[PDB]
Each structure stands twice: as structure tokens, then as C-alpha cells.
Image (cartoon, rainbow, N blue to C red):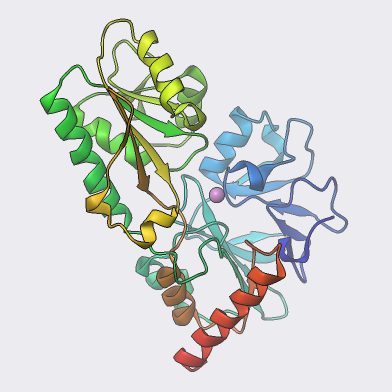
Length: 341
Ligand code: NI
């Protein structure tokens, strides 16, 4: 049964609530982004309206085979009307197509739903800057001071060079990149841009990136693995038994795999800095874990909320233990006392 934190009071609306059958009183279902925890329950046999970004709507049509008549895409940064209620979609800085939703309730209340997001100062000069917010449905995926990780530009700086060094020394070395969903497209588009290669991947994965509206995507990706030296592989496959296995299927073309597993947070971020990162080696196979987060760090979140000054906050993530819920309100209170709202 749908939790309270996936319902927008005063509307017929829900957010990323597709796995509970038909919700009672829901006239519109909002999907924030195309990650399976959020769209779980959608298929070609869904028959209620779906609202989402243009890009998320490509993925529903093509990957899930949801019917064109139920998908309502909306432009970003644009004041839209939806069953008489003003809504705005803003970019979440999460994965491609991912939005935050502003709801302007008839009664005069205003509600921001972050979705999954990575807080950025650029968000402080968006449509949010002009008015007050009463309820914040917040992505608390990293709501604890231990959660520090570097900026995305830093990780992509390291990733390029680490890769670009390896192949200028040994031009018969492969660059694999691990993936299971959307998101994290820079990691691989960046490395492959520098090396000169298109990115090679499966037909399935090739179908997925074709939906994301990337400029000139044709020029950047291929299914032709023989004609590619920056490959993509399922994240599960990025171990020693899986990379070996793949190294055979190259057919005498590459004599070394230099992988990347983009991870979110890992307890090694609490101690080791990004520039000091190294690989797990078992011969010619070197697997890099790098901290590429598509979620806010503790300080990014804090700054975002202390700017927004919302009257009530509602965590959408790590809600399932009284220890996590307990710990989160303490930070929210400290943030409110610090900033004097
Ligand atoms: Ni997500």
C-alpha cells in the first residue's frame, strides 16, 4: 500500500508510485526518472496518465512498451497546467531525463519533490528562487556527515587521464565501463571522446542511449565491438572472471582491460582522496572503483535546504529504520537552528 511520502496532499497526484496496483484517488501518476525502483510496476498494460520529462517518456514508449496515449511529456522550466494545478519540472542533475517537480496547490501551499537529485548552486537561480516552499520531499540518500565525495568534474578529470594514460602507453589495451541503468553517461562518453573511439555496447544498451536526446549520439556510440576500444559491460560482469571471459571474446585484438566501476559512496571515501585511487589487479585486469555520485553529498544537501528554508521536510529515502529516521530529523533541526528559520 502506497506510503504517505509518495502522495501529494490536496491533489489527485502521486510520485514514483507504480508498484501498488491502482492507487485510490490518483488521477495522475508522476514519474521523476527512469530507474527501476521508481518505475517498478509500469508496463504496456498500464492505462492511467503518466507525466514525466520528454526523455523519460521516450524510455517508457520504447523500453517498457507503454502506449503513446498515456504518456504526457512536459518541457522543463515551463509553467504547465495539469488537472487545474500549476506544475513545473526542473532538472534534477541526477540521470538523463530526471526532474524535480514543483506543485502549486490551489490552497496556496507550494511543494517541491526532489526525486533523486544532486544538489547544485545553479539550482538557486532557477524557478525556485522566486518564491517560498512549504513542504520538501527530500532525497536523503546521503544524509550523514561521513558522506563526502568529490565533484563530478574531478572524477571525470581523473577518469579521462587514467584511461588516456593507459592507452598511450599500450595501444592494445581496452577500456571497459560498468553499467546497469541510465545515468553516469559522462564517465563513458568522456573517456571515449578523448580516446577518439565511439563507445561500444550491446544492442539493448544501444537502444537505451538512442532515447536520451543526446546531440549527435550516432557519432558517439556503436554496436560494432570490433570497431570499438571503449566498451560497456553489465556492472555484475565487472569482476576478474567476467573481464577475462570478455577478453577472450575480443578475438586477439586487446591484451589488457582497464576497467571503471562508477560507485556511489564507498567507505574508502572517508579516508582516501580521489587523486590517490588505485586498481584491484589480477594480472592484466585492473578494475577501478571511482566515486561518481548522482546524489547529493551531505554538505550539498545541507546548503540546498538551508537556502530553500522550507517549513517542513519529508525524507523519501532511508525511511525504513527508526535509527535512520531518528538521525535525519536531528540534522534537519540543526540546519534550521544554524540558518535561523
Ligand atoms: Ni535514481
